[PDB]
Image (cartoon, rainbow, N blue to C red; front, side, top):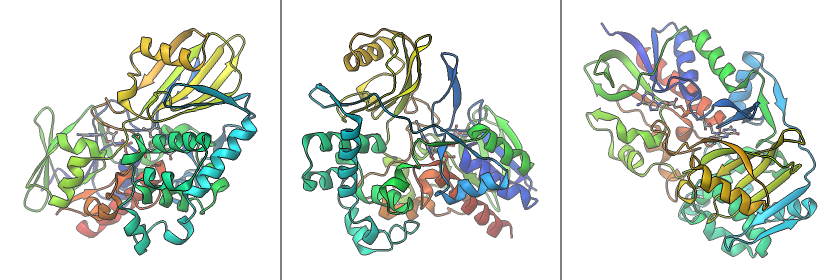
Length: 432
Ligand SMILES: Cc1cc2nc3c(=O)[nH]c(=O)nc-3n(C[C@H](O)[C@H](O)[C@H](O)COP(=O)(O)OP(=O)(O)OC[C@H]3O[C@@H](n4cnc5c(N)ncnc54)[C@H](O)[C@@H]3O)c2cc1C
């Protein structure tokens, strides 16, 4: 009697995976996507005549779920070559910019990182069960900043590790939950070189959008875009989904894959469990944005860190040449520190870092300003990871997926895929 067997809300990797799992079981499947595009927090675009990535793009074979999908659909890796750096910079909170030899730069960040994750081997024997250990549950009382003050790092190492960690937090390190960082490093084999190789090294052949289209075509599910969901009501043996144009779609089961910071704008009747509402209100930490800057001068191959109080926390050469100039890939930890769609502020901060250059153009994506992300990658605040099962738990015939709800690579494409497989199995148990 329902319009569809299962409705999936959201066309990111969590939604595409769930829709594919449901479709291949023969269920009549519908996916509703708020934007006029798919991919969610993965978005490939173009700038200054080149391909650029505004969100997620990089993967690794140490991430099980996304790698198995690439095997399923015959997609290989595309390498961004490690390359030698000409300059590595650190910008401290005082505003001073230092140029360090790239060989000193790598040694100091590794020392600081390895001391911060010294206990990951003991505390997370099973990174896919983060709360297995007691130590893990007692560490969720502390922030990443709490550990860094005890490590006794030099001024350079602390600025490096704090900038790198502010980037993973999308926020200041005093807000950043400690165990979530150790668990992610545990997922990469408890090893520094293995984990660092997963970061900005390999992209998917055909792009993230190609693998998302592969799964959705394979699912057979009906896909609608520019259809935001505004409310969900639990009916008798199903659910009622209301779109922003007030039309009602009925289904036996509905799967939520929207980012956690967007649940505030969807109404649920009846109300969800209070443990769920708590993560509904708090949200996830990251307030990041992504920015690309085109400069007339050819800076070669540069990398820079800036600490939490400064705007351009992660800068790296995307491409360079004398004819082109330099295209810089920049990640902003916090929205409050700079408006990426304000060019004049962007030009000043690039010039502060690289005095003497004039920006020819800028391309930005402010994920925190976007109504359908309201934040960047998944980052847990202090105490959140221990209550993660409140966010994963099904509420009647409403299932919940998404990178934030995953147990492994929660800050990654892989975590979204993992949650999609779990959601598909929970669909299989309700429809039987
Ligand atoms: C700048 C940035 C860089 C990143 N780089 C990497 C990387 O290099 N490697 C890696 O592994 N991961 C990376 N990530 C993380 C990765 O992008 C995410 O973890 C993953 O895409 C999350 O998948 P998801 O489906 O759970 O969320 P989403 O991709 O956000 O999917 C949710 C979908 O639901 C839609 N939606 C929202 N609200 C509604 C609504 N009311 N109704 C209908 N639809 C709605 C949204 O528009 C969206 O399409 C990055 C993230 C960011 C922000």
